[PDB]
Image (cartoon, rainbow over all chains, first blue to last red; front, side, top):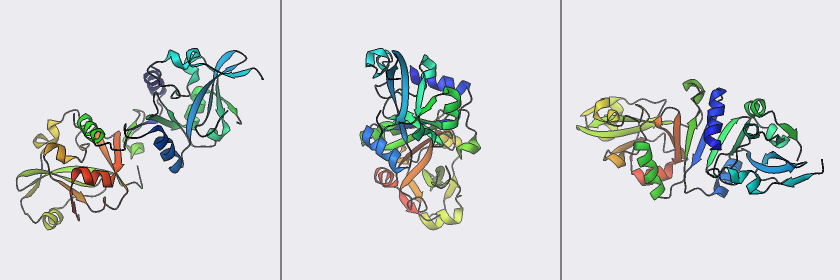
Length: 141
Length: 147
């Protein structure tokens, strides 16, 4: 399970992170709207193929995305983690040997907030801690 | 478990609520949520009956204030064995303010009714729950008191 693995990873590194679980009465849209109204940027992860190799692109949920670039199929990566909902993959590509590309729109913020296993379960940690742990390549998108 | 019972109760009522859990790397000091008025539950005995007083965590109950609010002099703080100790998985001082689920009358400080949300410890000091004060008041039907 990527979430249990993630928490075990962050705990071993003594990371201060929050887990925000929304009740089932909340829709995914209400969650994204609440984060926005709060002045928070909700980050989303998209799986790409860069020169034929799997990578993660991390960018604001409200935004959209070498010349050898294509989106990965669910069976190529996301589908391999069944307990983790499609679109709720945490941006910790390092745990699976995937390079991580992060939007500079996200690096401007004090924290990074993202879905963890489902659209209802969020996780937040400082961008500085995320950047030190993951070592992503920052990209302008 | 009071927390699982509360979530089952709120879900059946289609309530929008958040659960905020702090990783073990967090100290109690860095956990301590400023600006937003954290609510705490205190168990009292009113005329020999167990009741809940819900007020800001920075506030304290006094006998003169509860007596003026309730109208009775038979007031005392409950022992842990009288209520909180009966729920071992739920830490002392982290009891959610849903006294209605246990037949306890709930008394809520007017300082909390001024806020859009109610935020409280839920089972531990590292785990918080938040829902609108309006939803809480409609579900619990507390008596609003000046403390």
